[PDB]
Amino acid sequence: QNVKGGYWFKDSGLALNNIDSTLFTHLFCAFADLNPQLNQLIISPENQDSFRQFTSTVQRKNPSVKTFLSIAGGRANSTAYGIMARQPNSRKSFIDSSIRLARQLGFHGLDLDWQYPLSAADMTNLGTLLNEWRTAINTEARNSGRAALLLTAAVSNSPRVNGLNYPVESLARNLDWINLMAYDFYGPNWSPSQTNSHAQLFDPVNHVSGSDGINAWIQAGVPTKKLVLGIPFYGYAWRLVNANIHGLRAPAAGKSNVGAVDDGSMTYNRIRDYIVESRATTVYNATIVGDYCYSGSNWISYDDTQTVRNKVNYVKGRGLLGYFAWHVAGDQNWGLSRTASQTWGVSF
């Protein structure tokens, strides 16, 4: 089966019951947390009510949709995961609790979003963790007579992150697939001084792109059929230094106040509304395969219809397993989700 994936989190402002699960094959419920005292996977009090109903609810609209419980994510404490992965006993309690929790709540899979291991030792220990996790998943399948839980991971665009190499052999051998985070290449909180496409499929300038990421993962020895390309339903707004200079790599002064206070981020839906209200000029850049818009001193990078269509055709043509969206609530009336699904077409 090909993957048409979508991530959801409670604080996204889309009600669980309003996720259009007909546009996806796999939905990822984000995020379960690590209890550092127990070294067990848990669900926070705030997430409890929705996470327990996640699978049954989304399956009402589409009984064939499969669900993942996603783990950790961008706001998690990476040191807690490093500690957990350090020892056989803490790995075992994490592994066992994750499998129990997935089964208890009806999830068909577990998705590790550790962002990111902090040292080479942590990367090595991640490799060991996945070895043991796979064995335990296979054993539970055998013992219960049930189909094995799926195991995936959301990973950096390239297999080298923060100067550290992923345990690529372990990822390739143990995971059903990897979710490539082909976005956040640039953003006001890490690259404030110039505009850039945060998810560009191509990059002739610096080779920071989704295609270059795919290529790096392939060169590292992960098979093409285990790659799923991430697509963002959001973007970032920069403040331009000079409103007249508004292409890629235009001088900037950090986040624009049209975006979120903390990081300048905006959902695709919010960007679409902004384009209408400000009469912003929009650009599809065919070289990079990405969109941006500008109005006055405000400049926003995002993926619109043509970019989503072209990305999906590109990865389909290349023999990747599929795509996923971060995150479903960011879409405008399921526009990009439908574009992606229908562009892919038949999902097997």
Image (cartoon, grey):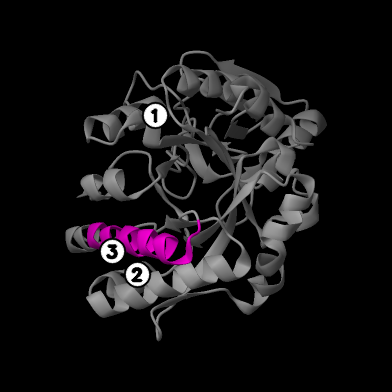
Circle 2 SS class? helix
Give the main secondary structure of the magenta stretch. Answer: helix
Q: Residue at x 44, y 27 (%)?
A: 249
Taking the image as shown, residue 129 lies to the left or right of residue 120, namely right
Q: Distance from label 2 to label 3 (Cα)?
A: 15 Å
In the rendered view, tell whether residue 92 sits above or below residue 139: below
The count of marks equals 3
Residue 82 forms part of the magenta stretch: no
Circle 2: residue type:
Tyr
Q: Which residues are magenta?
A: 126-146
First reached walking from the N terminus: tag 3 or tag 1: 3
Q: Which tag is nearer the camera, tag 2 or tag 3?
A: 3
Circle 1 SS class? loop
Q: Which tag is nearer the camera, tag 1 or tag 2?
A: 2
- Residue 301's spot in the image, x, y percent? 57, 32
Q: Which tag is nearer the camera, tag 3 or tag 1?
A: 3
Q: Which residue is mark 2?
A: 81
